[PDB]
Length: 126
Length: 126
Image (cartoon, rainbow over all chains, first blue to last red):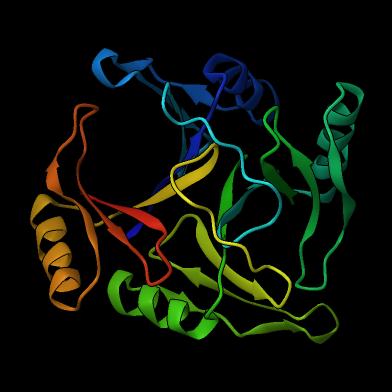
């Protein structure tokens, strides 16, 4: 038993795909489509481990206000401290929101926290 | 680069820990605590791959109404079709909500969908 994937409801599917592909080295599979339900999805694969399922459908439309009970974030590890700093700066210069500057957290992670094109939290870990 | 963990805001931390430990074979680490911010957390490890970070803090209190933009669910694989059926039934008999009966989905997964003690979606995959 293990986590096969984590899924994300998205409003602009292609914009999101090319974000994770550009910045986190993800590989996309073929677009899946269910015209009847207005549903579209991609599975993004990383080096190994869990995949990210990005999906959208015409009825999934509501935005959540702040920090609430439920799924909180995902953490992508980069392997080193230097890697977190380098990626956080590439994202900054490309205009993304840096919610958390790189640092050692009290629970022992060297990470930064950035927001994807639709505001979702991602911890960029070593 | 890869997904190190997926995090979940929780209202009853211990209840949630023993759920994932009981049903999905997860192993918990030591409770982390930041008394100043009212924060508590556990990291649950599976066979390998991404971990599940279950956390709570006195200010994270709001519930989200339906299916919205943002993190959608996580999928735990069990390895076989038979395993999905067996686990979905154990969960049913123990009173958990079966949102989706086991079946082959159009995107090629044999899975069921159950709700954890706090209503979060989990796809139980083969």
